[PDB]
Amino acid sequence: FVSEQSLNGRWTLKFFPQPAVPVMTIEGAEAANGIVVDAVVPGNVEIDMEAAGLVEDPMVGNNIYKLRPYEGYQWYYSRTFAAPVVTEGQRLVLHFGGIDTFAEVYVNGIKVGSADNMLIEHDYDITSVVKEGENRLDVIIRSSVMEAQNHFLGTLSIGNFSNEESAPVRRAPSTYGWDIMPRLVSAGLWRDVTLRVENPVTIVDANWVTLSVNPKAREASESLYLQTRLPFEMHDKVKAVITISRDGRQILRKEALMRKFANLFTLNLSGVDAWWPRGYGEPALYTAEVSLVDVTSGKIYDTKTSKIGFRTVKLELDEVNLPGQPGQFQFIINGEPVFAKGTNWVPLDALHSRDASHVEEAVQLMVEMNCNIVRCWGGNVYEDTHFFELCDKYGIMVWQDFAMGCGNYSQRDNFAAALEKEAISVVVKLRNHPSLILWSGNNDRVSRQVLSRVIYEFDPTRPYLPSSPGYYKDPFYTENPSQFVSEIGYHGCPNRETLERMFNDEWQTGRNDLMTNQVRIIFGEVPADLDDFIFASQSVQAEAMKFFVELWRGRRPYRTGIIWWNIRDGWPLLSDAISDYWGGKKQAFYYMQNVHHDVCCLINPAANGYMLKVDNNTLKDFEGVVEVKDVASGKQVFKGKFVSKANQMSEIATLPMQKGQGMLVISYRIEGNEYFNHYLYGEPPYKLDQYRKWVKKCGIYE
Amino acid sequence: FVSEQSLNGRWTLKFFPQPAVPVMTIEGAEAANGIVVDAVVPGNVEIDMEAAGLVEDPMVGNNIYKLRPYEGYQWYYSRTFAAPVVTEGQRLVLHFGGIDTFAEVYVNGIKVGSADNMLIEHDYDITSVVKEGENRLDVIIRSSVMEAQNHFLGTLSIGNFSNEESAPVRRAPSTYGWDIMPRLVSAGLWRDVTLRVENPVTIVDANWVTLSVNPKAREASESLYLQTRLPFEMHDKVKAVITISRDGRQILRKEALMRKFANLFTLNLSGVDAWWPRGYGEPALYTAEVSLVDVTSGKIYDTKTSKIGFRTVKLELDEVNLPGQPGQFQFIINGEPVFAKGTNWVPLDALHSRDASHVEEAVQLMVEMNCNIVRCWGGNVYEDTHFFELCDKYGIMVWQDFAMGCGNYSQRDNFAAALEKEAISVVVKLRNHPSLILWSGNNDRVSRQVLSRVIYEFDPTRPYLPSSPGYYKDPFYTENPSQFVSEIGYHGCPNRETLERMFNDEWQTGRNDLMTNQVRIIFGEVPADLDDFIFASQSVQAEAMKFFVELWRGRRPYRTGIIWWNIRDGWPLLSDAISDYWGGKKQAFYYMQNVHHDVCCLINPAANGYMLKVDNNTLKDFEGVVEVKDVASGKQVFKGKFVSKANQMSEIATLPMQKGQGMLVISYRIEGNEYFNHYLYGEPPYKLDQYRKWVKKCGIYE
């Protein structure tokens, strides 16, 4: 964009209870009896009120329930802005990255738009209403909860675990409450507000599509679907300048005279690397830039730049074993069947204006874990562009769920038009990121028509799948027929430092019972000491998660992927996450890390023994040695060389059954690098002090 | 509702020919040159004009054809009403139970609505337009026939037996003419007009769904889908009070704090009886009441009460014998396959404001007949709530056809939006009646999309079936393959008292020939005497109907149901009904009554004799004796005991073929109760005097 003048910073926020007739004008907003405080954009209204000392910190104890009255409040944002320089023919666009949710937008007392979706951007042409000098921007938000009473719900929209208030509105269903995730509806301008100046000649969209890729020949066929705004007097007088580069070095430069507003450019490239997920290769990214330049004067009218990756994606459905069942598929990246291992992406923060501050660390948790895939939960908002940029950079594939609740939705025209608008917005915005590999829904009007037609018309290169949503050794897990398990979870108690900071009735804020259960089956009794209960509850979560991934990794090539719930909490809570809201890595995080390795030696239970395997999630063969040794006595159970064939599971040896309870060490070395693992044999209940000494003498985990 | 002030009574009706430009304003209505007369609401405009002596009685002779000019007239209803007490926050709703059809509704000279469907209710919020003191209500109806010329018809909408004027409008197709049913379009406010006052806290809908039922254990799982209007200041401060009772005794009382506007309550009940159709058990009904009560003050904001029945319905489709053919299904009520026997429901009156006055007696005709099912014809209007209440009370299942004509309809957006609005209105209004068991239609845009999507979203507990629409011993009836015959009919001449009251050209008002035919095949010659022709024509209809039901009852379990056309006339006419418009029971009515018994001994023709059967449409076993005796000579053909197994047909004996013509008596006694039947053997033509003596000496029918 020619000019991007930010409107972030200090605004004026006036809040008041919403009357029977909602306030939708500036006159009623300034006449209403309310409280005026300073606000920060981007932000949440609860953050502004806590800065004013009007609400307590909702992250401690039961303070979150004290935000209940504000769900029926209205929120009046207002600020003054200076009008940027607009010459004749240019357009001034007021850009909202996120309005939660129902609001009337005014510029100089003139309504410029009416917003009704918190998950998509909002752009309003304010060229004709802006004035010279000081201008006025007013946004009057009304109660999201009360808007639901403007709709009549179908039978199948009531009673589902999704809140009925979430059914007729386009908002993140998690904000209304889920499992233990607490109700925090909130409101406000939770993303950037900016002013954009566009030339009469401008780029509307630049769609990059990888037609084909030959990784060995270092070649790729890349298409550019360029749509521009082009006055006819500029036809045959503007040229498009396409530039592909990597690390400063220019790979390709193509110029073409713009004779029409929409064009397709096919670039056959040489000496370019393919984009691969983690383990299967390098996440090669190339800077793709297109510019509209005047042929005579050289004036640059617009320029769009993004980092793309040459990659092809295909979902291979298995119709021989369980045809059409959830999980009977496998991702084919660059013609190679990949094994998916990763986490489900939950909200990063109940106050979603703080999501961007957590994106960096949260994605890094997947890097240390070595996740090659991540499934963004449909109950959460759509993450912004920077999240996908990090997944592009670190080679983490993205499975994107369209925002839906666990329960049926409307089948009428009004809700379909709102979902089509949302789908077209999200698809066009994200369809150029190589990390994104799959759209997912869940004649049901939303998934089997509206979302499918949008993908068919705006993203034909990605698959669209409308489906797939006590003792960890129970047949419930060990005899699951799903080639690709999606949401597998287990509860763990957060670290003591997180407990003493977030905090009976406070712990409840049968799920808390589930914690005490799992410790009894594994360790016999519930430890009276708090520190002993934390280590025991975290060790149960650690072994259970490790067992799940090792099971799927060891049953390849039938098993094709495993996504687990989850990697990080979005609120200081007692849940199934392996890392809490403040960055505390629980005991499970380290157990899984030694199993998500590119080449991992593991043990699976066998009929008359233990099966020592080695899994390879790369495209190269590896040689090494592996040594199995009982922890307690130190006896060597197995030691020998192994060949890890590329992109497959390899069986090494069948170990004899050990006596009673105990632990085995897995010491294997690859190319001079030492890697470590373990296997808990025997039958529960175990002695907690014995399991503690096994971990300590193993010398792997603290 | 807090206040229901009726607006029924005397109105002011001004009628005039509709100009080229239809009158749609109060100013043009009062300026038009017309006639002003007193009117009665609810009513039909023809009834008001006959009270003024302006039209003759359209029930005598050819007077109905003199109402032709009024089809192009406009009708201007007008009255004054006092405004009920409305406090701050309350809503005043003007309720129309039925506007026929196209009208502009004005309150104090301000248009509050525009109506375009005579089959559904119309509600308009007149809170902002009502004034203190005397108010004005004006309804300007225009010509329904002329509105059709505002549409272009498809090829398949022209030429069908449905009138082309009925295709593009939402009106009862019967009003335009059907078979001999005469054309009487009519107009007016044919149902109640009332004023309703709603609190800010009010009940929008209370959907009762029987999830499951265990008749033996006297248990049932009942769900309540409650949708309310709830100001946020009332959240957590209003409670819902649910009460299930029967005959004053309270069965269940549940209270729940209203924390959101829409909720699902599941009630697991004990000591409750299931609802059964006639014969299969008791029509147990329970008073289900929900109220919104202020937790502090105890103020009752709203209360909705209705009688429900714990019942489950399933349509078992036969895909082995004739897969997908009409009639190859059977109703499963409470897990039991039921045998359906009943009548088709035609209009109760061509002037439909008189329907409510006939509902009581008409439903009683099905009670004396012992019908356990009734199919409301799609050419008729949707009956009101009281009709379904009587079917709930007397255990008569209801098969509801969506209002459609025999012929294809439009496939464009305008007609689909009008039908979706009508379907959503009718379904939400009737989905709580236990007697209702089936919705029926007939990629055809109406049945295979619009109606189906409405049922899927607003009534998932009931089946939706888009289909099934000379000598009575001709193979045309005796070799019909339909397990469930739906519209089986036969003509009979009404009683003499009905002829001398309704009345060549008058009798015509080849169908009248059909009467003279059927008497010739059965009795040889056409009786010259009128009384002799009436008895002969009614006896033909009586034996033919009796034969049809006995055929289906005797071929169970393959045959699953039989609905016959029809039980009652809606106008003094010569038709196939077994009871005329003035309540006169024709000879067929009594023949069918002795065959619709819960346990009926009957005879079916066999290959080399007669098959003596006993049918059981209950869930209990019965023992008795049966005696067969020839009428003319008095010889005993058969006598012995029989065991009637529950809910099945049982063969008793194969009787030898009797000589020549004659009649058999069927004298069977069950639990000390005497029941009677007969069988006409031989081959037509018969002597009418001989058949008369057979009936007289049989001692069953007068």
Image (cartoon, coloured by chain):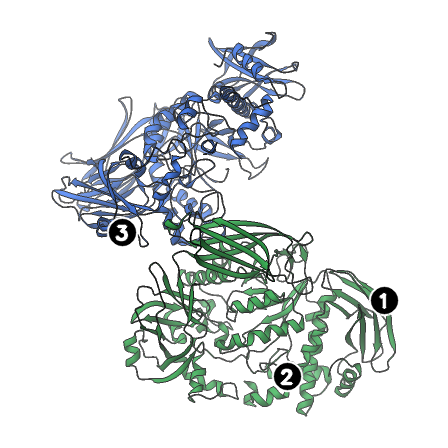
Chain colours: A blue, B green
Residue B472 visible to the viewer: no
CB within 8 Å, label 2 to label 3: no
Mark sitting on residue B147: none
Residue in the foreground of this view, choosing between B452 and A78 = A78
Mark sitting on residue A24: 3
| Above or below, comparing residue A203 to residue A365 in the picture | below
Badge 1 amino acid: Lys
Residue in the foreground of this view, choosing between A685 and B618 = A685
Give percent across and percent down for residue A310.
37, 29
Badge 2 amino acid: Cys
Mark sitting on residue B641: 1
Q: Are marks 2 and 3 on the same chain?
A: no
Q: Are marks 1 and 2 on the same chain?
A: yes
Q: Residues within 10 Å of mark 1 (few under 14, many from 20)?
A: few
Q: Are marks 3 and 1 on the same chain?
A: no
Q: Residues within 10 Å of mark 2 (few under 14, many from 20)?
A: many
Badge 3 amino acid: Met
Q: Which residue is mark 2?
A: B493
